[PDB]
Amino acid sequence: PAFDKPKVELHVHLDGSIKPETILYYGRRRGIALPANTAEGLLNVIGMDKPLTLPDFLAKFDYYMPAIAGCREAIKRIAYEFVEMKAKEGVVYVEVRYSPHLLANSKVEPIPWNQAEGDLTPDEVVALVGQGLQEGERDFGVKARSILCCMRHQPNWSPKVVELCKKYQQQTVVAIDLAGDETIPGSSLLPGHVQAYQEAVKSGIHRTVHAGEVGSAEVVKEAVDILKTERLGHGYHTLEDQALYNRLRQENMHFEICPWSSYLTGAWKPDTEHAVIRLKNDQANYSLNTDDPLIFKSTLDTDYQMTKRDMGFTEEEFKRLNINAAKSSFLPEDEKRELLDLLYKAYGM
Ligand SMILES: [Zn+2]
Image 1: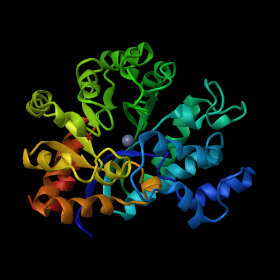
Image 2: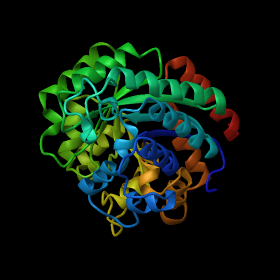
Image 3: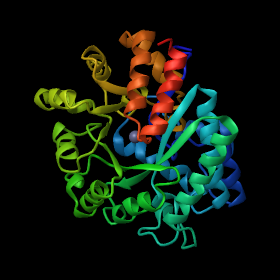
């Protein structure tokens, strides 16, 4: 264990943190053609061993999402099982993100994963995921919060998403995200997406955006200045624009680093200095995350030991980034202080 103290996770998707044996049970009980009948072999088609491309990583979801989406018991259980997982790895606070439309099967265009029309609405999916997170926290003692994803290819969804972020603000929902295929040109300025971050600014909904993961620094630059996000998912290619980088450094922008994810998705070619090193060297505001452990065959200790032996991270630095993650969390002022006192008490400060 590279860092055996309480950690914080801000960027990990519920979509990509399902147990391969939970998928298997629901794929069977719904009679769904899964690319495998065996847990360890399911993880061989879905798991990634080498670097690929962004469209190919997103393609892996087409394998197993039909078994989960549209079924109630499967939706809530993976939430409960997700927080369980995070507990076993030393996480005291976790913000888990997911697209309620991609788990629904009714009142959604398009019905994802080629499902048939049913009765599970996006507004219902958030009430079921939140229930699993609420029951998990009570069983495992780790504070767990949803973030609702926009899809870059469906700007028609994002009007409903913020709006959902607002109905469930007093539940588990703390912010809105913009995920999906960043390789689609100009998907950041689609009108559907922009009302969403605009209505989020008015009504005080927190904002994070996948930006700079496989695109240019212009991707990050509209996310910052147009959508006015407060955190960057995979802020890697911000470092190609030093003027912008040092501006966000001066404005204490938080970067949601995912080291092992960044290697397997091709985001970081292994010949390059990883972005997180100088963001450590510049003492920037960043955190370490798993992104999608099922698809990357990872745990959060995978991402911590990637830093430790390969990028020269220390226990000292591990303490600082997790405290920065705690004060760039989307928790309210009272709970985010209570979380800082947890980490203060465990870190010797
Ligand atoms: Zn992500």
